[PDB]
C-alpha cells in the first residue's frame, strides 16, 4: 500500500550538482510537490554509512577499489582547481573518466548520492516499509565495474539489485530508457536469479552499440554459464509510437513475470524515449486517458510485486518532470487505490516558467503512426524464455505464455 520516494535537502543539492543533468531533479520533485503528491508518499531517506570503510565496502560490492579511488581523486582534483598531471590524465583515461564522463567538483558525492538513494529504496522494499519506492535521482545503468560510461559513474541499479538478491530471491530488471541497459546486463550476465530486460533504440554508431545482433553471421548473446538465456533485449528502429512500443513490450513483460515469478521488480524509467527528448528517436508521450511508459508501469504494478522505479536518461528537463510526475501519480493510484487528479494546467511553483509557453502537463506533441521486426523479436524472445525456463527447471503454462503474444 505504501509508496516511498527518495528525497532530502543534501540529496537534492547533490542530484542537482552535475553539469549534464543540472537542476532536472529539482524540477521533477517540485512538479510532484506542486501537484500535492508528497503527502501520499513516504520519504525514504538516502542511506548513509558508519565510516568510510563501510561506504567503500558497499560500493566495491560491484565497483573496483582502484576505480572508486580514481573517482574520489577526480573530485579532489576538480575541487583544488589543480590542473591534472599527465600521470593523472592517463589514470582517469584508464577508467573512461573523460569525454562524456568528465570530472567536476562534486563528481564522487553526486555519483554516490544515487547509490545512497537506490540502496535505501531497496532496504525499504526488503523490510516491507513500502510496496513501491521511486528514486528519480537514480537509474545510472551504463556504469561498469571499472569504467564510467554515458554520464554514469557508479551503478546505483547494480548495487540496489545486489542488496535485493542478498536479502530463493529472483529480481526482474526492466530498462525502459532509450539506451541499452548494458551495465546492469553485464553485472548479472552469469546469474539466473537476476533476469535483465532492456527495450531500446539500436542502430549503427548509436550508444552503446549492445542489446542487439553482434559480431563475435551476427549472434544475439543472452547471458552465460548459470545465467545463459537470462539477458533479454528488444532493439527497435527509430520513430516508434506509444501503441507500437506498448504492443512490443507488453507480452514480453507479462511472459517474464509469469515464468520468473520475481520477488522484486526494478524498473529504469529513463525519459529519453519521449517524442520531445532532444535525441528525437522514439515518439513516446506522457498522455493518460496512452503513454507507453504509463502502460508499462501500470502492467508491472498490476503484478503486485515489490517494485523499485528509477530515473535515468531524459534531456528535456520539463518533459522529464511531466512524465515522472504522471508515473508517480499512477504509482499512487495503482498501489494505494487512491485516484490522484492532476490538473492539465501546470500549478504555480518555483519552476513554473520552465513549462512555457503552453504550461500544460501533456508534452507538446501530436502522435501519428510509427511491426514485422517486432514479430521476429517476439518469436526469438518467446524461444529464449523457453530455454531460460528449461535451463532453470521452471514450471509454467507454455500455452498461456504463447497466447500473450
Ligand atoms: K533500455
Ligand atoms: K542475468
Ligand atoms: Zn538514455
Image (cartoon, grey):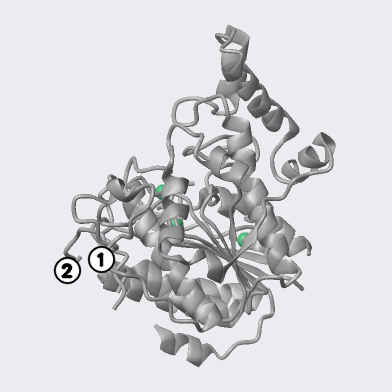
Q: Name the residue rendered at 44%, 60% in the picture.
A: 32
Q: Name the residue rendered at 78%, 61% in the picture.
A: 166
In the displayed structure image, the side of residue 51 where residue 100 appears, left or right: left
In the displayed structure image, the side of residue 24 where residue 309 appears, left or right: right
Res 201 visible:
no
Q: In which quarter of the image is residue 325?
A: bottom left
Q: Name the residue rendered at 42%, 85% in the picture.
A: 404
Q: Which of 90 and 6 is in front in this view?
A: 6
- Say whether disc 1 or disc 2 marks the residue closer to the N-terminus: 1
The label number, if any, that marks residue 369 in the structure image: 2
Residue 130 in percent (x, y) is at: 66, 71
**Hey, which residue is sitting farthest front in the picture?**
348
Residue 174 in percent (x, y) is at: 51, 64
The local secondary structure at tag 2 comes to loop
The residue labelled by disc 1 is 241
Q: In this view, does 151 lie above or below 305?
A: above
Res 112 visible:
yes
In 3D space, how far apart are the residues under numbered discs 1 and 2 (Cα atoms)? 7 Å
Amino acid at each position: 500500500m505504501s509508496v516511498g520516494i527518495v528525497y532530502g535537502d543534501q540529496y537534492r543539492q547533490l542530484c542537482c550538482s552535475s553539469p549534464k543533468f543540472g537542476d532536472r531533479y529539482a524540477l521533477v520533485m517540485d512538479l510532484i510537490n506542486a501537484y500535492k503528491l508528497i503527502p501520499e508518499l513516504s520519504r525514504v531517506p538516502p542511506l548513509q554509512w558508519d565510516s568510510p570503510s563501510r561506504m567503500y565496502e558497499a560500493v566495491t560490492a560491484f565497483h573496483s577499489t582502484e576505480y572508486v579511488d580514481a573517482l574520489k581523486k577526480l573530485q579532489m582534483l576538480h575541487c583544488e582547481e589543480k590542473e591534472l598531471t599527465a600521470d593523472d590524465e592517463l589514470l582517469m583515461d584508464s577508467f573512461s573518466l573523460n569525454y562524456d564522463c568528465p570530472g567536476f567538483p562534486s563528481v564522487f558525492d553526486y555519483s554516490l548520492a544515487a547509490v545512497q538513494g537506490s540502496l535505501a529504496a531497496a532496504s525499504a522494499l526488503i523490510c516491507r516499509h513500502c510496496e513501491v519506492v521511486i528514486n528519480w535521482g537514480g537509474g545510472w545503468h551504463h556504469a561498469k565495474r571499472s569504467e564510467a560510461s554515458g554520464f554514469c559513474y557508479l551503478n546505483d541499479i547494480v548495487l540496489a539489485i545486489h542488496r535485493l538478491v542478498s536479502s530463493q530471491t529472483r529480481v526482474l530488471y526492466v530498462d525502459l530508457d532509450l539506451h541499452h541497459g548494458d551495465g546492469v546486463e553485464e553485472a548479472f550476465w552469469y546469474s539466473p536469479r537476476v533476469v535483465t530486460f532492456s527495450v531500446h533504440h539500436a542502430s549503427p554508431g548509436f550508444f552503446p552499440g549492445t542489446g542487439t545482433w553482434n559480431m563475435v553471421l551476427p549472434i544475439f548473446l543472452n547471458g552465460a554459464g548459470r545465467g545463459r538465456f537470462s539477458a533479454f533485449n528488444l532493439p527497435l528502429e527509430e520513430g516508434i509510437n506509444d501503441l507500437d512500443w506498448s504492443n512490443a513490450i507488453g507480452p514480453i513483460l507479462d511472459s517474464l513475470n509469469i515464468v520468473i515469478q520475481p520477488s522484486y521488480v526494478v524498473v529504469q524509467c529513463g525519459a529519453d524515449c519521449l517524442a520531445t527528448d532532444p535525441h528525437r528517436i522514439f515518439r513516446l508521450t506522457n498522455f493518460y486517458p496512452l503513454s507507453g511508459y504509463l502502460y508499462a508501469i501500470k502492467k508491472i504494478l498490476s503484478w503486485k510485486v515489490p517494485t523499485l522505479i528509477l530515473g535515468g536518461g531524459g534531456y528535456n528537463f520539463p518533459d522529464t518532470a511531466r512524465l515522472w510526475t504522471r508515473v508517480t501519480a499512477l504509482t499512487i493510484e495503482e498501489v494505494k487505490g487512491k485516484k490522484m487528479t492532476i490538473s492539465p494546467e501546470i500549478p504555480e511553483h518555483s519552476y513554473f516558467s520552465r513549462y512555457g509557453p503552453d504550461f500544460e502537463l501533456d508534452i507538446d506533441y501530436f502522435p501519428h503512426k510509427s511491426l514485422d521486426s517486432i514479430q521476429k523479436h517476439h518469436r526469438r524472445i518467446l524461444e529464449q524464455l523457453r530455454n531460460y525456463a528449461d535451463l532453470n527447471k521452471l514450471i509454467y503454462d507454455y500455452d498461456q505464455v504463447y497466447q500473450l503474444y
